[PDB]
Image (cartoon, rainbow over all chains, first blue to last red; front, side, top):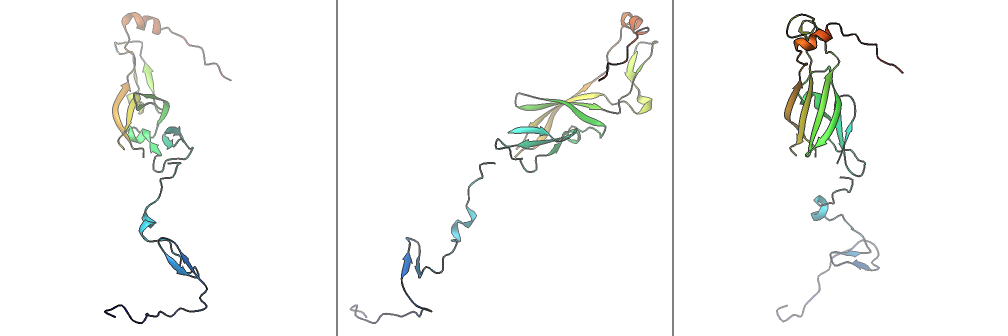
Length: 50
Length: 128
């Protein structure tokens, strides 16, 4: 492992793996697990009426 | 922003998109430190401040042909309710605060004026 020759670690995934949907923020297998993003939930625009 | 007279005492502010501003409905009669018998007669905007005329439904005035003080409020009948003009301003939304309060006292009567008044007669108002 010190020379860079080794075994890959494996994470089990339920169901049938077909692809991945990768954005500059997220990589979702089969496009599952899409969230609102907790950081920007407290930031919004002032409505035009007010 | 626009101002709207909701009733005889309250004023609500509205945005340029025709939406009301929340917690803007102000009772100007109360804010002007005037009792329930008072209602807003006229409003105007000068400088940036709101100028409001108030007049009571409980006002009672007297005319006595004798003396020096011929015209006066009927204090004895709980009608000593003179009119007032109040200047209001924004300390903020819209929060009104009283600047100046001016009372409208009864007219002064001269001996020369009182000689006419003594026998002055008036025709009942024209109606619809």
